Amino acid sequence: KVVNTGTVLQVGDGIARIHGLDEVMAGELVEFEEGTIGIALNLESNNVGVVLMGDGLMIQEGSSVKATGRIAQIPVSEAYLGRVINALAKPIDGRGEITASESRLIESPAPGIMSRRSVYEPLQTGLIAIDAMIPVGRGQRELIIGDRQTGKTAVATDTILNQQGQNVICVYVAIGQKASSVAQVVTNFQERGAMEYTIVVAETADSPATLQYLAPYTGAALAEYFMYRERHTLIIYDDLSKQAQAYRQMSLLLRRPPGREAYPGDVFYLHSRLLERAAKLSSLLGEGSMTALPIVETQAGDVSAYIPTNVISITDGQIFLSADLFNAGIRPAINVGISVSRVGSAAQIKAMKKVAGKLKLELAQFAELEAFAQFASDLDKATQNQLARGQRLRELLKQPQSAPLTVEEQVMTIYTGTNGYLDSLELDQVRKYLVELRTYVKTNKPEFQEIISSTKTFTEEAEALLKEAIQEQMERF
Amino acid sequence: NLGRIAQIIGPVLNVAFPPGKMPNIYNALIVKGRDTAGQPMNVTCEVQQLLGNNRVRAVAMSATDGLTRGMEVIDTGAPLSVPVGGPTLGRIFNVLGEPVDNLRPVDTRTTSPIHRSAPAFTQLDTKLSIFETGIKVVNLLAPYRRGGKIGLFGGAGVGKTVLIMELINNIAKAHGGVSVFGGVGERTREGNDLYMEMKESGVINEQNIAESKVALVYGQMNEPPGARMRVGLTALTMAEYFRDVNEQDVLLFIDNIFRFVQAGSEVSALLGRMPSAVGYQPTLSTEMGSLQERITSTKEGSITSIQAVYVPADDLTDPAPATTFAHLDATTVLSRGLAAKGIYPAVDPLDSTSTMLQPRIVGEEHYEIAQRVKETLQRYKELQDIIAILGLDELSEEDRLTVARARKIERFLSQPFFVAEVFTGSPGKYVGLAETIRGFQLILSGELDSLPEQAFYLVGNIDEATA
Ligand SMILES: CC(C)C[C@@H]1NC(=O)[C@H](C)N(C)C(=O)CNC(=O)/C(=C/c2ccccc2)N(C)C1=O
């Protein structure tokens, strides 16, 4: 049957040239004798170019192939929420199979312009430096940039953690990450009960390249099942860089014409799709949304690089992280100076705007004289006020990994420094101030904390009532 | 006609017809079978080669996933025809002219080929009118020639879009003619936004009384490459109607025309040609050129196109944006470092021209100052690398004056936007010619040497810079 079966011509480097199979469709799954799954892309004149999804060491020139007839479908449901999933949606954790009732496609068109609405719904991440100057709202695409070891994954680890139950569903997609390292994470997510609402769509380095592509695509489809259901999602794709690389590898193995850094001619339709399929659907579809936070590693702080260039131009903001501003105390390292957010403060409440907006104007003025501090032989107080109130807020902006702060905890804290309380204090000390003060308010004053959130804003009372709090509390240092 | 798909290699179709039928080049074909159980026909391509051997190749405008070999293709018999006319205003269009705004079908009078031979040499004109925008950097250091084409250049995130919005606000909502905005390779948000924003100002149809003065065609990022290579041409075919059929004066807002080249980049090597400078196609100059000389003003009317162009890795030597420039009567080159300073709109007062900076077309006061402004803006720029290491202690009392004034210029050259009221945090301000002209003449005269720098930063008029 040269119609729904075929012979294998050649298997070279995870790609196979199938012969026959006239009926195949572009994008259809084919099944090998030794049972190896692969997709079809080159519907060339008399042979089919198929990209394997596994160790092709198995395919043998002469073996036949069946045409699954299915255009790469993936199972989906609720049955996940706590299962480190593979790439063709099959468990890799050893807890049994997954009860899939429906099954959505990996690649599907993204929500258009009628099916969408601006972003107003906030997205709390537990990072004082993010949810106050880098406002990420639901449905909005926010990029995470940084070299090797730049606390980026950490920005992500805390964020998914920082999601109050029933609030936001999360998908953790690892592309080309290490097994171990994925595990060190998939654990630090359980020990805090956060793995009861997050999937771990991950494909290690060893895993064949024809997968690190779909790593996100799956990870995105699995999430789109909650969106169209009025639910909200957050997608973290650990490195789109390692996915772009896996792309290049397939085009060259399919013998397709390359270009800049050997990158194919459809390298921009790898992000302008993952990141588009994410959005805030109209209320005439479910108000459901999906916020994607894609990571893109850099080389030598070289932003203008192709992949990082392209992705930045697809996302609604970036959270640059620096390799020079680590040990300098800044932990986590947020270059809030270049880190932007196209949605605007629109992704924040009023209680945050009142403080954050103001904190914006501050950590924006210091930036202009910062380089002076070290060489300040005789500056004016009108500047000192800035090189004073400067490195103060920063230490508030510093955060210990694994500890995401609530929104209350977020606003109250900014309030201390932003309002001149932590002013005349010593930087190499302020860290413990907040740590101490926070727990102090959570214990003795959790009555005010619940006043803050519900009211969603600081009343003229709680202010004075905060004033009495901090002033006397700093007085306990 | 009827041929069969012969090879499907991504968004490229190699169709094989009978030795007689030969879809002429650029003639759009249309394919019969596609997505998951159900028969659509969205798969429309555009012949681009006669490989020979009874076989044209073609780029699809829709996704080929699911297509098959042998599927009957069909030669419509002419090029891809978008429906144009009055019945396109207030609607969001596909690269194929299909309504994408869920408001019923489009009741147009006649279609029209996105493939039209630009105006002849005797259908052109030389009139050079101004185009007051309302920003203290354009109308003063590089004005807008009506009919002419504006090139709003910059790198990834510099305020180009915010720049195309303020223009629709300052000029389009108040423009006394029809306008069209093309969506060439950009985010969807920006679309959703620019829509629900143009709705509130009622630039669109609040009621179907149809008093709209805008026609929208959106092919965003996600679309395959054979979509952003031509939505720039739908938007324009719909604009090349109001220009000559209703003798109207139309505006052509293309939010990034680069995504139009990038999109062609991607069908180049794919179709089997030999790449060129920086991975681009050999046919880069033939592609964005044939579609910037239809976007012009003629005697029959006019097209004031205010087009944006992406600048990869911050480099202007880059073949993609570089090419544009020729096709421009003005340029607003934005900076990433001058944007890293907070001064917005981040526009480099030095690298930004306009053919109409002629005293023969605006005046002497507009002519000198602009330069006087720039002159000092050349001085300080050639003083930086010097003072940065050589300090000021030995600088003459006649050169330290360049410094203060300049820092008063590069700042008085800031101006929040009515659309960017969320990035600046302060109310926008409309600063026309005279208000700007004189405002600066009060600076070049050291009439304001006392006042500080941040006195002109994010300020409306000179007075607002003295309050
Ligand atoms: C991964 C599969 C399920 C989806 C693909 N579809 C696409 O990515 C694009 C957006 N579409 C819809 C196309 O029609 C073009 N297809 C491909 O380029 C591709 C490219 C591809 C490259 C390398 C390995 C596999 C595939 N297709 C696979 C389509 O079938």
Image (cartoon, helix red, strand yellow):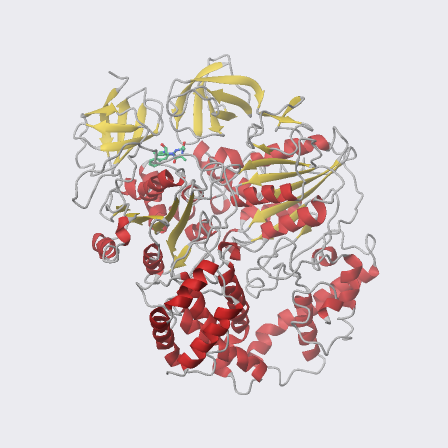
Q: Nearer the viewer, residue B86 or B155?
A: B86
Residue A215 placement (x, y as % from top left)? 31, 43
Q: Quadrant of ligand 1?
A: top left
Residue at the image position 52 percent from the left and 62 percent from the top: A353
Quadrant, the C terminus of chain A: bottom left
Judge left or right: residue A305 versus residue B119: left
Residue A436 placement (x, y as % from top left)? 34, 75
Residue A322 placement (x, y as % from top left)? 40, 65
Residue A228 picture quarter: top left
Residue at the image position 63 percent from the left and 41 percent from the top: B199
B399 relative to A355, above or below: below
Judge left or right: residue A74 versus residue A233: left
Residue at the image position 76 percent from the left and 55 percent from the top: B357
Quadrant, the N terminus of chain A: top left
Judge left or right: residue A430 versus residue B440: left
> Is residue A334 among what the camera can see?
no
How many marks the image carries: the answer is: 0
Q: Nearer the viewer, residue B203 or A124?
A: A124
Residue B240 placement (x, y as % from top left)? 69, 32
Judge left or right: residue A390 versus residue B324: left
> Is residue A127 among what the camera can see?
yes
A81 relative to B53, above or below: below
Q: Nearer the viewer, residue A8 or B370?
A: B370
